[PDB]
Amino acid sequence: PIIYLVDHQKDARAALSKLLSPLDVTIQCFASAESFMRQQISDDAIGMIIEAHLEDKKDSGIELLETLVKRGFHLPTIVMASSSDIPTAVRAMRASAADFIEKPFIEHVLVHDVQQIINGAK
Amino acid sequence: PIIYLVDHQKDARAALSKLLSPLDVTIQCFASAESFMRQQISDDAIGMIIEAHLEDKKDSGIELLETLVKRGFHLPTIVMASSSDIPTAVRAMRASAADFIEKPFIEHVLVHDVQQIING
Amino acid sequence: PIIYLVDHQKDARAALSKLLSPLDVTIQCFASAESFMRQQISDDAIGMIIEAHLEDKKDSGIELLETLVKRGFHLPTIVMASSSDIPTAVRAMRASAADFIEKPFIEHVLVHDVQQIINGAK
């Protein structure tokens, strides 16, 4: 079981990976939408975590989600942002995000959201 | 033509530079206000883009603009900020900024302001 | 006199120590709560400066303060945080923080806070 994390913040990829390692899943990370788009989506992928504003480009992470959904890829996605206004949250939900989490986040919220994806997958 | 970019975030400098590359302009970066004050403003320079809170010191980017204005240097300046309250935006405008852009930013908004400086 | 600084951001630690160095106090830094909890609190320590969201984990720095308070340790503490809400600020004040400073911060605000700790310690 693989969950792709797309976030341009090095510390975030590090911190998030550590927090979720003791969960039954592999966290494969990407520093940008461009980098992730070169990735052959694995059949073992069950979910995704995406920073809403990749590289400080407002809503670029959500656009990535919208693009993937448009291309038929339907993986439960958790959208996260350390900066967010109401329209961004709404756009995220309309883009089918399973949840939108503001950062700094509460670890149990994230852990719970991921476990749910893990369980719903099996 | 040159546009000075003063932002303490390395990755940010790179991204903004890359984004503005296709435009008829060269971006010269500086990681801090002091680093910039060690600079004799060139005659080929037509504008600036400054992070409002350099090194987490609130409004320091705007104070740089304010001081530059007092020093006679007048270049259309785009002030950008991720963290921002109303007083900061108002200060930037009072400091003569051509625009105040919140980050995360909308790509074409920055591109448009820069092009407007180029055309000017 | 020593003032402990706990902040996961390498750049912040350097910038804050530089800014405060001129004052009559020595700043000793820590990259994490875990690392600080290993430190034997010196008798010369007169205060602390703690990032509220250590390693992106919401309120983890405030949690640290709460733990110190429960251990009978009472050193005037300045909690600092970027991107925070009311509850976080309220939680830090309840944890007995001497002050709560939003970042980006106004330089003299932090300096005056520290100067105050120095004067009240002698």
Image (cartoon, coloured by chain):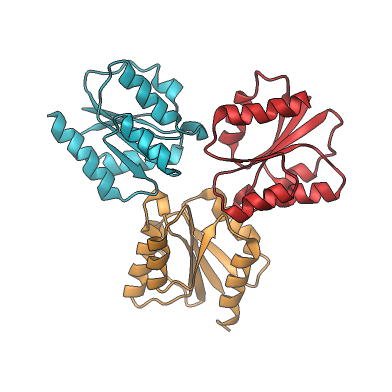
Chain colours: A cyan, B red, C orange
Task: Using residue C57 as the reference point, say whether residue C113 is left or right of it.
Answer: right
Rendered image quadrant of residue B100:
top right
* Residue C56 position within the rendered picture, expressed as x and y whole percent measured from the top left: 40, 49
* Residue C41 position within the rendered picture, expressed as x and y whole percent measured from the top left: 43, 71
Disc tally is 0
Q: Residue at x 36, y 70 (%)?
A: C68
Task: Using residue A44 as the reference point, say whether residue C47 is left or right of it.
Answer: right
Q: Residue at x 72, y 19 (%)?
A: B24
Vertical placement of residue A107 versus B43, above or below: below
Vertical placement of residue B20 versus B74, above or below: above
Considering every residue shown, the one lying at the far left of the view is A122
Q: Nearer the viewer, residue C29 or B91?
A: B91
User: What quarter of the picture does the C terminus of chain B occupy?
Assistant: top right
Q: Residue at x 45, y 32 (%)?
A: A59
* Residue C66 position within the rendered picture, expressed as x and y whole percent measured from the top left: 35, 69
* Residue B15 position within the rendered picture, expressed as x and y whole percent measured from the top left: 57, 29
Q: Nearer the viewer, residue A12 or B6?
A: B6
Asked whether the viewer can see residue C38, the reply is no
User: What quarter of the picture does the N terminus of chain B occupy?
Assistant: top right
Asked whether the viewer can see residue A46, the reply is yes
